[PDB]
Image: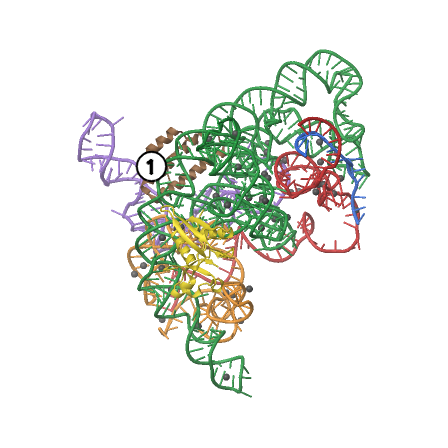
Chain colours: A yellow, B brown, C purple, D orange, E green, F red, G blue
Amino acid sequence: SMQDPIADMLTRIRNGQAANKAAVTMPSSKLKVAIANVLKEEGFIEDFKVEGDTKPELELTLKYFQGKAVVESIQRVSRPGLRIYKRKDELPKVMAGLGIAVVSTSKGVMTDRAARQAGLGGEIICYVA
Amino acid sequence: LSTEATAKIVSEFGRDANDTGSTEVQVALLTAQINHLQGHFAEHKKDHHSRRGLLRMVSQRRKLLDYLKRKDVARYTQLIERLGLRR
RNA sequence: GGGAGAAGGCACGCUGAUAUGUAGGUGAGGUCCCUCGCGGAUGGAGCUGAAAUCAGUCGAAGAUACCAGCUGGCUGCAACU
RNA sequence: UAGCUAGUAGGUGGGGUAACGGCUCACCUAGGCGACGAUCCCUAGCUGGUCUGAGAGGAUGACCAGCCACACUGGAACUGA
RNA sequence: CGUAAAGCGCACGCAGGCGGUUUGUUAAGUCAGAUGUGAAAUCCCCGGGCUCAACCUGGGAACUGCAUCUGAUACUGGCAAGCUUGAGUCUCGUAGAGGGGGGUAGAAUUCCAGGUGUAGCGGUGAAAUGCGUAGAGAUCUGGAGGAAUACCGGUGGCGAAGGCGGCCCCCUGGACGAAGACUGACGCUCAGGUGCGAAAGCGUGGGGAGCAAACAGGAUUAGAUACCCUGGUAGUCCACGCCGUAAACGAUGUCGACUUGGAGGUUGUGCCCUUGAGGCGUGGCUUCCGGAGCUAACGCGUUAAGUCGACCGCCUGGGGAGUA
RNA sequence: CGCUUACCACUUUGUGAUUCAUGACUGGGGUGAAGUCGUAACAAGGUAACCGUAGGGGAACCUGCGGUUGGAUCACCUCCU
RNA sequence: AGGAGGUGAGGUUUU
Ligand SMILES: [Mg+2]
Ligand SMILES: [Mg+2]
Ligand SMILES: [Mg+2]
Ligand SMILES: [Mg+2]
Ligand SMILES: [Mg+2]
Ligand SMILES: [Mg+2]
Ligand SMILES: [Mg+2]
Ligand SMILES: [Mg+2]
Ligand SMILES: [Mg+2]
Ligand SMILES: [Mg+2]
Ligand SMILES: [Mg+2]
Ligand SMILES: [Mg+2]
Ligand SMILES: [Mg+2]
Ligand SMILES: [Mg+2]
Ligand SMILES: [Mg+2]
Ligand SMILES: [Mg+2]
Ligand SMILES: [Mg+2]
Ligand SMILES: [Mg+2]
Ligand SMILES: [Mg+2]
Ligand SMILES: [Mg+2]
Ligand SMILES: [Mg+2]
Ligand SMILES: [Mg+2]
Ligand SMILES: [Mg+2]
Ligand SMILES: [Mg+2]
Ligand SMILES: [Mg+2]
Ligand SMILES: [Mg+2]
Ligand SMILES: [Mg+2]
Ligand SMILES: [Mg+2]
Ligand SMILES: [Mg+2]
Ligand SMILES: [Mg+2]
Ligand SMILES: [Mg+2]
Ligand SMILES: [Mg+2]
Ligand SMILES: [Mg+2]
Ligand SMILES: [Mg+2]
Ligand SMILES: [Mg+2]
Ligand SMILES: [Mg+2]
Ligand SMILES: [Mg+2]
Ligand SMILES: [Mg+2]
Ligand SMILES: [Mg+2]
Ligand SMILES: [Mg+2]
Ligand SMILES: [Mg+2]
Ligand SMILES: [Mg+2]
Ligand SMILES: [Mg+2]
Ligand SMILES: [Mg+2]
Ligand SMILES: [Mg+2]
Ligand SMILES: [Mg+2]
Ligand SMILES: [Mg+2]
Ligand SMILES: [Mg+2]
Ligand SMILES: [Mg+2]
Ligand SMILES: [Mg+2]
């Protein structure tokens, strides 16, 4: 059964990148919208939108540079079977700074580079590079 | 199960006699089917292919009764008292 | 089902107290009504009566006399009464 | 090693220790621990630490320091803060 | 964990593990700060002193931890109110060797009682044992009884698996398809536990046509307790129980979401002049070939062995041994 | 001071569990030198192998039932289309 | 080119 919608979204994005799909559609969620906001701000995707009022569908527009894809690696660090919680002093750095570790902090969802400046830790949702 | 029997059970247990999907209605239908098959399995003791369906109905009824007990105990007690069940 | 009473071990008398004879059993007179008598609820008078605990006590020995399983192990035969 | 425990879990009231407490006694409840491993068997003093390992980790606890147990073996009590 | 060792034979399911979506609140886990403590010694950093070093020593960092307080509320969890997309229920129908019980029909083998009729029959690579003048084998009639249902029948269908085939009746389970109505996570997996579970085997009571272990004979062979032939018992069958084992295999655990395709088969449905078997689209199951991708390779390949989450089971050199 | 009671140590009796050492004899496995018998498996291994099961047999093994493919292509004649 | 019917020392070891 579906027990990880965030991982489902990440796998949909990865499969779209692999199959050279321009758009990806999925069910919407308050956390999926926040993750897509971070992705759009970091430039890994072009745009995201939500359509509907009772059964919202979230649509993402993928980005392809020089014919290939942009998101080469995308993981789900924290999973329902194993929750990952790290403080600010030991936040990870994906690809030595060339990647993003999406972190849910006490103020919202933000990258590790933005969470360390604020000086707060939290949950490590996913790694993107 | 007979359509007339299902309609009577729905009218007896539901509100508008058309919901036919409530927990009480489903439990009553499963109990009626089990009680009707009691006489069928008292003679054909080598019918495990149909006894598996009876076991599935028992499991579904148990799950529905657990959900009803967790949600509204007052309705669960009345349902078990009316159907003659013990748990 | 048994073996098994397996093997082996402890208490056993008497007095007083618990209880001027206990728990229990039987059960009167006198009380209510009652179809009303060889009746029932209430009641404990009186009678009988274990077992148990504590303390003390006498003898070498308290199931003190008669009565009243010796036990275990290996094995052949027959199943057994 | 899948069942253990009858002072055993608790309560009431005495006694007792410098002090709370079944620590102990008399009585009343049938409870208590255990699959998150009770009970039983084997081995073993523990820690700060040491060696290796980049790191998580693995092995170990000699000499320095802290804690516990013991003084031929098994128990006992007095004096004494 | 398809082929090297590794997926329980298959299902139900308790504890347990995980869990769709919205709001509000609590603030436990988590996040930030502060306080106390985390002995000293030891490691490390910056220095200092024994003619340098080993050694000693000053300060600091560290001791990833724990307890309390002050707060933050994005996520999980506790509570309340909700939602339908998961799951489930009902109305209408479809196909199916789905299961149990009870009957019936035919072909055929065997045997018995007979009719016609005579010297062989059967079998093998070749023979023989064997059956036959006591009339076999051949052909016809009648009867007796057992088991299984030729074609259709097709990498076709159903069932969780094992597995299910003539026809009829009764009871019953499951799946799917178009329209509708309803509960609002009721959801997935599962140690232990329970149930089912090919064939063979055991007990009780029957039945026993054919086939056939064991067994006997005849052959081949240096030998043949086998391969071949002649007979044939248990068994095969029925009723109630027991055993719970298979190369129980897709050598691939269950459920869920996504990712280019082409040929069909089967089973429903929605339309278009069905204007004769036609065209388009939508579902389920299933067979084959192959793209990216994966893999040691073979090969898998929208029904994955590809891209991911949850849960359970299993393996850690070959023998000994799945044995004591 | 003495005696007695209550607690307990050394010690003794009976029946058990666990572990160690050894034991006539025996089952099975392993290592050895080109020992004896047969050639079951690897090709279609010359009866296609294999698992489960029961029986038999000096041994590999054979056969009966079910299951699996982790077996070889089999090759040219006749008939119809 | 499609469908149907059969079809091989009967055995003969070891190095
Ligand atoms: Mg006598
Ligand atoms: Mg003997
Ligand atoms: Mg003798
Ligand atoms: Mg005799
Ligand atoms: Mg005898
Ligand atoms: Mg007491
Ligand atoms: Mg006191
Ligand atoms: Mg007290
Ligand atoms: Mg020691
Ligand atoms: Mg290493
Ligand atoms: Mg240690
Ligand atoms: Mg000494
Ligand atoms: Mg001493
Ligand atoms: Mg003193
Ligand atoms: Mg192998
Ligand atoms: Mg293997
Ligand atoms: Mg399997
Ligand atoms: Mg949730
Ligand atoms: Mg908190
Ligand atoms: Mg903190
Ligand atoms: Mg210096
Ligand atoms: Mg320190
Ligand atoms: Mg919440
Ligand atoms: Mg939960
Ligand atoms: Mg059928
Ligand atoms: Mg049906
Ligand atoms: Mg199990
Ligand atoms: Mg059988
Ligand atoms: Mg039998
Ligand atoms: Mg034969
Ligand atoms: Mg012979
Ligand atoms: Mg097995
Ligand atoms: Mg198969
Ligand atoms: Mg297997
Ligand atoms: Mg399941
Ligand atoms: Mg799938
Ligand atoms: Mg199927
Ligand atoms: Mg393929
Ligand atoms: Mg693989
Ligand atoms: Mg080994
Ligand atoms: Mg065994
Ligand atoms: Mg062979
Ligand atoms: Mg051979
Ligand atoms: Mg062979
Ligand atoms: Mg041969
Ligand atoms: Mg072979
Ligand atoms: Mg036998
Ligand atoms: Mg034989
Ligand atoms: Mg099979
Ligand atoms: Mg030889």
Q: Residue C67 or E50: which is nearer the viewer?
A: E50
Relative to A20, say whether E106 is above or below.
Answer: above
Q: Residue E124 or D21: which is nearer the viewer?
A: E124
Q: Amino acid at mark 1?
A: Glu
Instruction: State the image coordinates of residue C78 (x, y, percent, origin top left).
Output: 61, 35
Instruction: State the image coordinates of residue E308 (x, y, percent, origin top left).
Output: 49, 52
User: Can I make out residue A21 in this image?
Assistant: yes
- The residue that disc 1 covers is B81
Relative to E43, say whether B8 is above or below.
Answer: above
Instruction: State the image coordinates of residue A10 (x, y, percent, origin top left).
Output: 46, 53
Chain under disc 1: B
Instruction: State the image coordinates of residue B27 (x, y, percent, origin top left).
Output: 38, 37
Q: Residue G3 or A67: which is nearer the viewer?
A: A67
Relative to D58, say whether E212 is above or below.
Answer: above
Name which residue lies at 33% across and 35% down: B14
Q: Residue F25 or E145: which is nearer the viewer?
A: E145
Q: Quadrant of the N terminus of chain B?
A: top left
